Image (cartoon, rainbow over all chains, first blue to last red; front, top):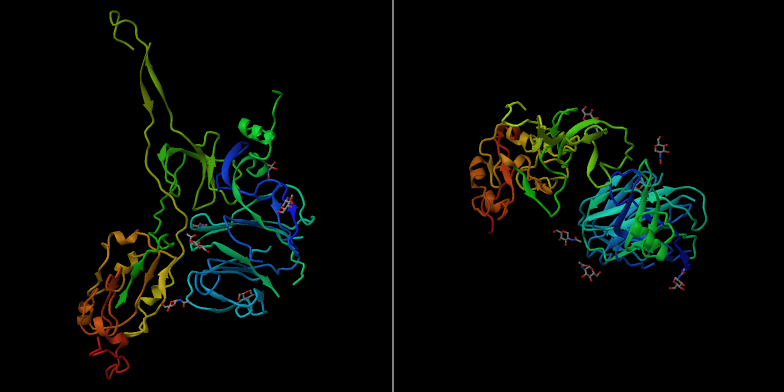
Length: 238
Length: 99
Length: 148
Ligand SMILES: *[C@@H]1O[C@H](CO)[C@@H](O)[C@H](O)[C@H]1NC(C)=O
Ligand SMILES: *[C@@H]1O[C@H](CO)[C@@H](O)[C@H](O)[C@H]1NC(C)=O
Ligand SMILES: *[C@@H]1O[C@H](CO)[C@@H](O)[C@H](O)[C@H]1NC(C)=O
Ligand SMILES: *[C@@H]1O[C@H](CO)[C@@H](O)[C@H](O)[C@H]1NC(C)=O
Ligand SMILES: *[C@@H]1O[C@H](CO)[C@@H](O)[C@H](O)[C@H]1NC(C)=O
Ligand SMILES: *[C@@H]1O[C@H](CO)[C@@H](O)[C@H](O)[C@H]1NC(C)=O
């Protein structure tokens, strides 16, 4: 609860659909800096330019997220719940209840009522220990839900490198200055993390098949910036 | 009596003109337009391994050289049409007029 | 030996490709559905997030006074939009003539007044026996003289 842990090298996502083979591409984008500083959980979390979420809960409690300006039946809000059948996305107002917990069935427990609604999207359920990562970018009006599922066993925050794939860029564009997590029902096993993205420059390595297998930050230390200047992963004496 | 009262709210929805796709041709210097990507070249069969979410192929100098067909998910390698210089070999015009 | 000019192979034809169109609008059944309301409570469903297929509109059942108040019908095939409202109602042909943006006359200002801007186009054709009672359809009502 409100702990702290270094982020190591995690939170790298594909910036575009372009296919590249055995190159080294230097890109400027919103990223999570290497060895950053995240807050372990075990919530009034604000939204600034995008967040990183990497819960490893065995259950599906923390599922659901609310985005908007006032997060009330005054400005349009969102809702993304991914249960065993289908994931539902609404873009309309919902008067918030006392707590953001599911009554269990999906209306009164978390909010008051649904009124003056608009575009609603559905798709296959997102779910498929089960390390699930998200990147909630909202550049322009095409809300991005970059994600990657790694059910590989690990620690509370293990090491390694793995990239994140896109999901959809829905036509939104309402004001999202504040966001909030949801949960289904405090002192619980709410093992989830938050990491704020930031403008940064990276040097990505593509294998011949076309997957990002490595990366180096360009502002972490002198060696890193030297690598970025030479556009290589090895440096000779000089 | 029925109306079709339209309204465009910033970003247009998927309601748009039907996409008048045509046939596909290969091994011929042709113009092309793959989902808004223009250019001219020769379209052949490719050995690329596109992941299920890319659309284009980019080389070192960032010139497109592989495109996936939107109708059927197939990757096509492209190549510019032939070009080059022309040189004329002649003896003196005092000698003859053959080249 | 002199270098004079350059040679270039000319393109032979043209080509253009796009994905499967699909995404049909579930609103064609609004057209030719004798119970598409009568005058007042038109089907609030609107044509949105599918296709702007206006080609079938002109090749539909023969209209009598199909009037487009927007852009020319020829270009309506490919212009993109976001949402398209559809009002389902039945009136008289003289009322169809009376229907215009910011116009008076019976239903045009008493039952369902057309929008002042009216970014849209009405499509009207004769119904007759489709929704007429043998003794006179008294179930259908119209405002003879509304307050304003
Ligand atoms: C993270 O932030 C906390 C408080 O802001 C600070 O004590 C700590 O040194 C920072 N770095 C790490 C690696 O936790
Ligand atoms: C969005 O909401 C914030 C407060 O939540 C406000 O300060 C801001 O002016 C609003 N508009 C934009 C464009 O950020
Ligand atoms: C998943 O949530 C939807 C949203 O209401 C609900 O209709 C559906 O029944 C839920 N799935 C199950 C298995 O209850
Ligand atoms: C939704 O639209 C109705 C009808 O225009 C309007 O009265 C209402 O204030 C809007 N907002 C809500 C939250 O109902
Ligand atoms: C890409 O394809 C090659 C050829 O089959 C294979 O050797 C390589 O492991 C693949 N890389 C992946 C799937 O990341
Ligand atoms: C597009 O239509 C053709 C026509 O039969 C079909 O073969 C093809 O599978 C369709 N594309 C997709 C992605 O379903």
